[PDB]
Image (cartoon, rainbow, N blue to C red):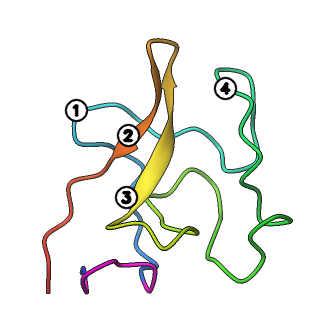
Amino acid sequence: CYHGDGQSYRGTSSTTTTGKKCQSWSSMTPHRHQKTPENYPNAGLTMNYCRNPDADKGPWCFTTDPSVRWEYCNLKKC
C-alpha cells in the first residue's frame, strides 16, 4: 500500500496528488526525463505508475501535464 519512502512499492497508481495522470516511465513527449528503467533498472519502473527510483520520500511520477513536469502521488502509508 505504502511503506515510508515507498521505493518498495509496486502498485498500479498512474495518478498524482492533483488528478494528473502519469507519463510513461518510457516516454518523453511532455517532458524529457532521464529516469528510465535503463537508468533505474532495479526499480519497478513500468508503464506510467507512481514510483520512487530515487531515495525520495514517497512515490512520484512525471506528469502528462505540460504545466506539471512531475509531482507526488496520493497513496496511504502503511
Q: Is residue 71 above or below residue 74?
A: above
Q: Earlier in the sequence, mark 1 or mark 4?
A: 1
**Segment colored magenta:** 3-8
- The answer to whether residue 54 is left or right of residue 39 is left
Q: Are marks 3 and 1 in contact (CB under 8 Å)?
A: no
Q: Are marks 4 and 3 in contact (CB under 8 Å)?
A: no
- The answer to whether residue 73 is left or right of residue 22 is left
Q: Nearer the viewer, mark 2 or mark 3?
A: 2
Q: Secondary structure at mark 3?
A: loop
Which quadrant of the view contains residue 67? Answer: top left
Q: Nearer the viewer, residue 15 or 7?
A: 7
Q: Nearer the viewer, mark 2 or mark 1?
A: 2
Cα–Cα gap, marks 2 and 3: 13 Å
For residue 67, the mark is: none
Q: Earlier in the sequence, mark 2 or mark 4?
A: 4
Cα–Cα gap, marks 2 and 1: 8 Å
User: Which residue matches tag 3?
Assistant: 13
User: Which residue matches tag 4?
Assistant: 31
Q: Amino acid at mark 1?
A: Thr
Q: Amino acid at mark 3?
A: Ser
Cα–Cα gap, marks 3 and 1: 13 Å
Cα–Cα gap, marks 4 and 3: 19 Å
Q: Secondary structure at mark 4?
A: loop
Q: Secondary structure at mark 1?
A: loop
Secondary structure predominantly adopted by residues drawn in magenta: loop
